[PDB]
Amino acid sequence: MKAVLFDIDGTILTEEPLIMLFLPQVYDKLSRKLGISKDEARERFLSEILGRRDSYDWHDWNFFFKLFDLDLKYEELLERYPHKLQVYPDTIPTLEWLRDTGYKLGIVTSGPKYQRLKLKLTGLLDYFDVVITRDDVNAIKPEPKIFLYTIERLGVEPGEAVMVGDSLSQDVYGAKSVGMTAVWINRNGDRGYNMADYEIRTLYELRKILGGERV
Ligand SMILES: [Mg+2]
């Protein structure tokens, strides 16, 4: 193996604390704008998100801010509250080990350009040889282009790369469809449907899967 590719959200970090912080502000701003209750604003906002699942726009918070013409920019929220982004304890030792061992490291995310800002703010950016977001290829997982462009940039063949992510449809199916090895990270004890080549609970388990020999 020569390269390990990572999903971001739910895989190497979580933005859930930031989501918990800004959603009430969204409900506040939306209810005040539309002259409706905060509960009705919540219903409308969340319904729109659910309605656009599995689509290009689903992975972009700014899409939803813009759709409701709200005075919010996710980049500004990120820069203001970077401590609300939480890096999993198993992330940095794993990236350190992989980089030191000689693996090329890539990010493949269906989120937009601010995903790179999230990596910068959490101190993870510099571990990666390349970071590919939706906005870099005009495509989302599991479209083959987003995986193929990433490994092309890394200079490796698909069979020389492993994808690690928490989404069965985006990460596992996406990676396998272009000939990569697929590792599903399952932090919350969900159902895996017998799909991935390997299933792990934390990134520390990658050491058992890959072994320790330099590449
Ligand atoms: Mg994810």
Image: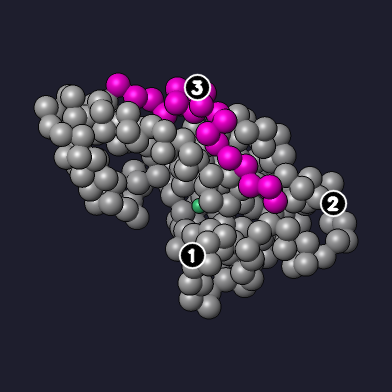
Distance Cα–Cα, label 2 vs label 3: 35 Å
| 119 relative to 136 in the view: left or right | right
| 28 relative to 176 in the view: left or right | left
Mark 2 vs ligand 1: CB below 8 Å = no
Q: Quadrant of the C terminus?
A: bottom right
Q: Which of marks 3 and 1 precedes in the sequence?
A: 3
Residue found at x 49% / y 60%: 167
| 89 relative to 20 in the view: left or right | right
> Tag on residue 80?
3
Q: Which residue is mark 1?
A: 168
Q: Name, please, the residue furthest toward the left.
A: 35
Q: Amino acid at mark 1?
A: Leu
Q: Which residues are magenta?
A: 71-91
Distance Cα–Cα, label 1 vs label 3: 32 Å
State yes or no: discs 2 and 3 in contact (Cβ < 8 Å). Answer: no
Q: Amino acid at mark 3?
A: Arg
| 166 relative to 211 in the view: left or right | left
Q: Name, please, the residue furthest toward the bottom.
A: 194
Tell me if residue 61 is in the magenta stretch.
no
Mark 1 residue element = helix
Q: Which of marks 3 and 2 precedes in the sequence?
A: 3
State yes or no: discs 1 and 2 in contact (Cβ < 8 Å). Answer: no
Q: Amino acid at mark 2?
A: Thr
Q: Which residue is mark 2?
A: 101
Distance Cα–Cα, label 1 vs label 2: 28 Å
* 61 or 56, nearer to the observer: 61
Q: Name, please, the residue furthest toward the right.
A: 213
Q: Which of marks 2 and 1 precedes in the sequence?
A: 2
